Image (tube, rainbow over all chains, first blue to last red; front, side, top):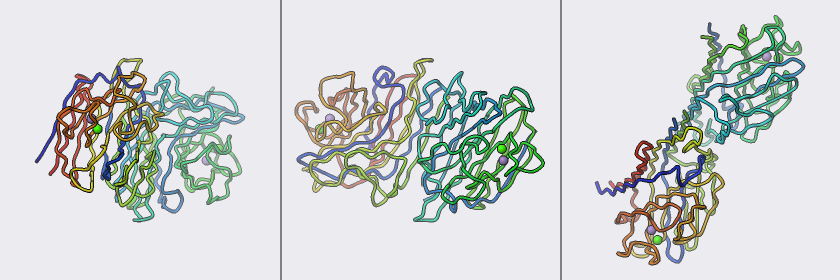
Length: 47
Length: 47
Length: 180
Length: 180
Ligand SMILES: [Ca+2]
Ligand SMILES: [Ca+2]
Ligand SMILES: [Mn+2]
Ligand SMILES: [Mn+2]
């Protein structure tokens, strides 16, 4: 029940190549935490 | 006109846990063009 | 749980989610495995590895694939070699050409092959094919000698729709080809 | 039409359809990008390239991804740096660590980056982060300074559910994070 939503217009064709890879990254520096993913689902459709 | 074949094939006894799927075709002393016009794949593994 | 799915309705010139080997490539929005030229091999694989079974749990995957393909020959009599859908190790590379279909190296069972293929064979090779000489659909596991075969009448230049489905609970592999 | 789909509900120790970079690896049914350790970068990419837009027709894809993730820190005060879902060239490699989240190199706009990312930032870097010092969700296109951000209160060690959707008709990208 606690939610955070963000919406933005982002013309992807202007910024990214036609073929891409997708994924996750995380970092620590002088402070830290464990960053872990438990599950992942993805669906894309190009007409 | 259709042709159907069915067989029991214990796949665990023949292929690795991870595989790549695909198509191949060849010609020898005789020949033909071989072409694929569309392809759909779906696999599901319980865990 | 793991699932992988994809569809390609029309192939483009730069189809980067496929691995091309031999002279297979995309043109005129089709995937071309061989052109009608002597002595060639072409293969195309999906780029992602698929998890077919897991040793930790002993579970095996179900899958379904459907595709439309065309064999275009000079005439109905002088045609070779045929076409395969196959399942092989992640590092698979083309194997013997000609009647071996780019996927096997013997009619003798080679457990180090680890590949099973559904072939649509248009040329009769006496050493291992059904003696009645017909063109046929077969299921091959570790050898070019099919464990089972069904005769098929090729319709030169006509598109064929096939569905191949594996169900892990009964371990049955089903093949259907239809000419509409 | 082209579609690419996959789901991984439980990651296993040999997860061959992912590319691991830096110190990312799979363990305990989890994908771990980072352990709770100083100075690390970890990334994981899905193995197949995906076709996001086409220059021949001008069409761009619709997509949706969801995932659940955990950030587990020594305490609620000393937490850094964050986590990203990103979209980048096929040959993408880890970039600057720490505050740059392994995906960008500068706060200056650089069209050469060709990366858009959704970040979940836990440490306030004063040169580019929102001036109130809050942890936040942000959309980044070719720069670590977000084009828009939403404040988010971290619940340490709790799992969060995320949905990111892109609609090609309106070019809008929507991010939703939920804690139970
Ligand atoms: Ca033959
Ligand atoms: Ca930061
Ligand atoms: Mn045969
Ligand atoms: Mn930020």
